[PDB]
Length: 360
Image (cartoon, rainbow, N blue to C red; front, side, top):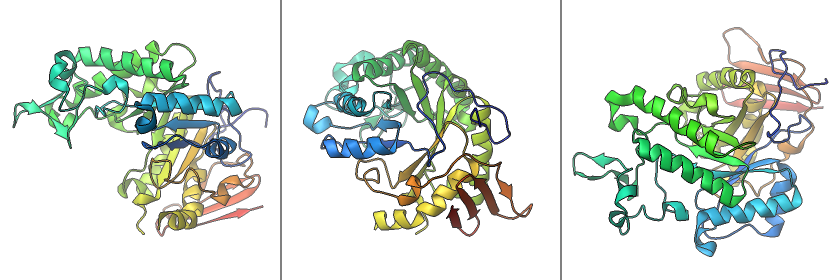
């Protein structure tokens, strides 16, 4: 047991800048933000005890501090005072120009016309000859080389100003459905933009791409250090999608990269804390079937500070230990899966949505 082993028995060799990893208990990732407030010291202590790897969300602290990158800067420092080697990621969306950081402050109806260069980075709706938008939030255009340069420099600036250890990049799609005849070009452009960002952050920084297991992200995946399975709808939680998650987790590990297996109970078929606490065994089991070295579980019912990060899910603190082998599909075409760890036996039926982890 001298080196962490992927489920195929190959050795996983982490990069020197990766977060800590252990099988002692369930490996965790946390992700949260609150527009209205910073974390209290006691909340920082709570989360720090439970993870070595987290991300501050897109609006955090914007009201008290005036800009969301200042929320990130504040929490990164607060966490690192406790655990200096905690890894804290800065969030930035590749698609929606959320106007919550100072960097994106111009992307509002009342300011964007005064910033013609920034405005020129945005997608136009042909039906109106006006900016495309979703509820008054504008759309970056990844096909615009000037946008790729500006955005990648901006994210690197946010990482540097906030003292974070890398970036969480939301969205890989580049609004391809708005220019479907250029879908392949969009995929390649996303790769180019991610590659610019990876270089501009400099050494020892983590690049995590949300849903970068998907085909649309194939040109971006090589430069990523990590990828998240967001499970953003019921379809992505189907028995077939979970089997695909497990395949993808192995492929990501074989590439030397990290995965985050994230669950939001908001996509469960069924009061959110009660439901999430009841369903934790099932969703944890789904992660453990496929878990790999330098993979992490995230659990809750959303992305705000109140969406689960501050609740105790007791299963996540129980002794786990290294896997004894890859999972077994109990019957070759059935939907029962098992896996044995040093301190636990995992059983899940992903067709019926039931599980049992026997902790030993």
